[PDB]
Structure formats: structure tokens, C-alpha cells
Image (cartoon, rainbow over all chains, first blue to last red; front, side):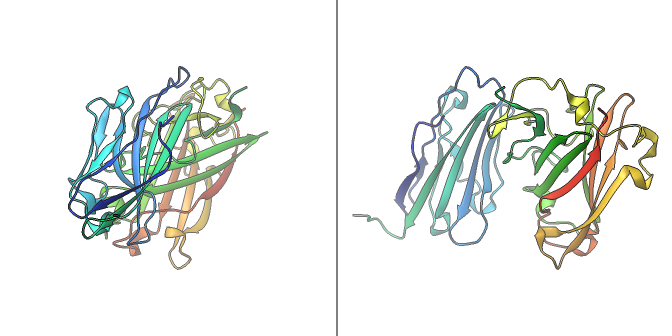
Length: 124
Length: 185
């Protein structure tokens, strides 16, 4: 499963947000590894929008237009147990709940991060 | 048993698992449950990338096929929609069991009832009216063909959502659609 609970990350416009998603695999989890990150924007009604994906040993991005080029996995070895990603140059539009799904049949886990972006620094 | 031998699904919340027009551009959620000689099925399809997010003006139909071998085991190659790494098998929790399906013919459409060369026959079809987006102002039809895109000793399920012609700049998305068929075994 994923090593961290549902959390809230508060950043400032322009900064970069690090969305942690580390996981441990069980001996039973013998199926192929899939890592999907979805987002439910606060500004609109869309829910569970695909942001980035790791399937069949390949990375697939370019799903959520407004987030183009600003999302990348942080680790250079996902299989090792780290699905974390970075959202660079945060904008107020990036606010919403980001979800990390890590699957290895029969294994499945997910984590929800509520990202908040503030015009200028301070959560004081 | 850790898994349910009466259910074959893609898991409730699959990741883009089809490359219909372009790589991993769609999510196909499919669940099949065996109730004696009848399989109760619920299918749902939604575009997540490319033209499937913006139905082209000329598009009139969007469809997918699932082709199985003589043991009822899915074949992950054209024209099967689900990609090779996609989850498909017995249900185990919110995921899929890694066991191989050994009672596959219990989920396959009966070939005596739906002969391989009979896909054009009304009987090899279950057609219903439904709605794009689930929006009752956007009616569409769903046709499920049994064993029409077969092999020999093989089986198949085909899903065609038609009447899309007059729906533009809309992502392709269906409601959970029900269907059923007589089983091979």
C-alpha cells in the first residue's frame, strides 16, 4: 500500500508542489504495475481527471491540458516504490484534490492530496 | 477462495486501458457475472484523450470488441480493445485475481444461440436505447453483438454506440449500460 495518509498541501502561486506517493508491494501483488494520478479541479465540475500515467513500463502524460508540461514523477525508479510527482509553477487553477492510485493485482492503493494554492505566500 | 469465480471484470475503476484511436485514450469498465445460463453484464466507455474527448463531426459510431479463445480466455490483440497489461479476470476485492480463468466458457456467448456466421442476425444482437453523457436529451443506441468478430472455436462481444452524428465537441461518454446473453456453458 501507500505509505502516507490523505493530506493537505498548501503552496504559493509560482512555487512547485511535491505530491508524495510512496508504496510498498506485497509478495501476492504479482500483476503488472499501474500508477495513475487523477485530479478533481476546484474551479470546475470535472472529477477524477487523468493527469499522468505509468502503464506497461511507460509514462503517459498530456491528459489534462491545463497542467501540460508541469507534471512529472519525481523518482527515476517508480517500481522501487515511489509514485510521487511534482506540479511546477503552481497556479490558482491547480487547486483541487489530487489522487494517487498504485495497483499491482490483486493489490490496490490510493491516496488523496488536497492541494491549495495562495496568490502570495502565507498559511503563516 | 480469495476470488469470485462467478465474476469477470476490469475492476471497478480501471485506468485508461484501451488505445482505440491513440495510445491509452479510453477507459472501459466491464463486469460480467454468471447466473446459470445467463451472464448479467454492465459496460461503460469513456474517452480520456484525443478525438474521444471531442467527438468528431463525422463520427456516427464508437465501438469496442473483446475476442476470446476456445477456453473463454481473452486475447489481448487486435481487435480486442483492452490493452495487454489491462486488468481482466476473476474479481478479488476491488482488483483482479492473478489466477487464470479456467471456467471461461461459462461467460462466453453461446454459439448455438449465436452462431459465428450469424452476427447480422437480430438474435445475435441485444439493442437498446440509452443516452450520451447520461443526458436524456442526447439519445443514442447501444448494440451488443454476440460472436460476430470471432475466430473458430472462439468467442466475442462487440459494443457499438451509434447515432453520435449529431453530438459535437462533447467527450464520448456512456452511462453504465446493462446487457445479458445465454452462456456457452
